[PDB]
Image 1 (cartoon, each protein chain N blue to C red):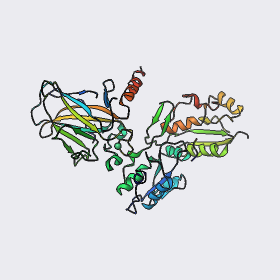
Image 2: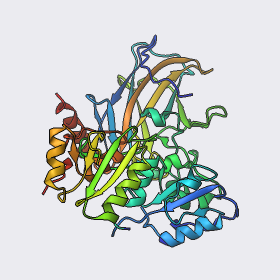
Image 3: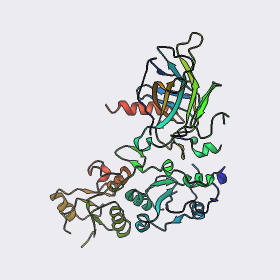
Length: 192
Length: 4
Length: 227
Ligand SMILES: [Zn+2]
């Protein structure tokens, strides 16, 4: 069964923020789509109106956006899997850097890969919580996503696992994130 | 092979 | 990197047991080695098709087309019409690396460049693209047109395909005339009077890429006389 992708700000009013960092990761709010480079730092901010309690965890899981491949499990192409972080399995697509308490789940039921990190409140004077994600496979990777568009699902959950917040966004791992972002963005306003 |  | 990424031979002598393969080479990712891939498939008890044959594909074997990319050859068109999946050769390689059959849906090759969509299109199950279609083929070339498009249209679910040289039918009973600039003016005038659309082979090919009957007058290249 495909995990749900419906926006759910929840009781804490959870929302997502995107930054930039040659652009290595850029975000289009018109398309709600992230264009980044292979194994590059992708800043994803967490904005909450109500500070969640301790023990709260942030899970990340990628699904395919098209209907004909939505039921297909997202994984890393066997080429990039045969050739390493350490705590991250070689089949996982999404990784987290900067956090030493990160977990990687494979799910004995669905068999989908996910990566979770304990929630932390904004630090010294911050207004959100930045998580640094990494995508270890190109969109055009044969054997993996294979040109299929994928959505990244970010969820908030308590210590047990019950849902508290959900947001999603499209991701394209390409060589030129800026060029492709402008290309699709115009390729969108030109329809009108 | 030959393309068309 | 090359010889290793090509992969080894399958230890499981029956890895590809029950699959038929129709390899095609684009006219000139790791490069496609046709005979090496054939050796990999044969070693895993895979059956190699000499050509397209719907007498084994529709019966015992699960047919698959192996190629390096999307191409405009006869085998590619026949599989696009019959709904046989177009799968990259890496699927063979990555499977021999693991000695375990991989999901070919992760190795689907594109259909081709669409004129209506102006981009390369990913493949989807076709399930016949020429259902209930009476076609009249008019050309001077018998082999690479009167036979080619006859077989491709027929394996695409066409209700009837007639082969007429450009010198010698029921007409009005047809739905479309697929011809080329060698069409006699008699067929063009009779078709015009009957309001019968006359298109070129690009309409058929684009129908195979998109996977559905597209507009006759949708693109200028669909005209037979397009010079
Ligand atoms: Zn990859």
